[PDB]
Image (cartoon, rainbow over all chains, first blue to last red; front, side, top):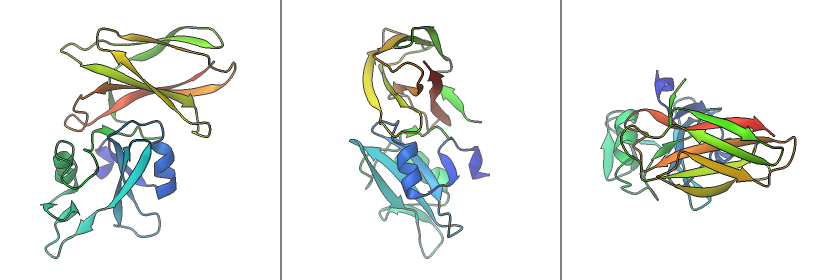
Length: 100
Length: 94
């Protein structure tokens, strides 16, 4: 289901995400699941040669957010929003990492 | 598999050290490109450079003979996420 999205890489470790992004540029990103904890997800984002990792938090009402001020019903809505408005991320989610 | 932008990327001429690569110019517009290249697997790192939006080719030179490279072309500012796209990437052995 989520696999249809360019930016959704499934289970990938933090350190592996950094390798996947190392061919990236500012705004290169991917969304990953924890290999150990099903349902636990993060966004990994490249900026100025480094990778910033943001846990996708779940609100008491089930909404998702990476930045408390901006909350969403679905992950696709969250990513679409943050692709144009950084809103707490170091930069926008602009360039989905090629899946490998 | 995800579709890419640009849509085509090819090594059109090569020596063991020096490549000419080509992708498809946009039907509409682009501001400029960023290209990254480096040894496949990421151990030795990646270099990044810009390409003017008037081009749809680039040269990459000073590569090591017989080595595998990952080359990725980004249309800078293109809304990849809106259209569910990734940057185009190839692997090439020199």
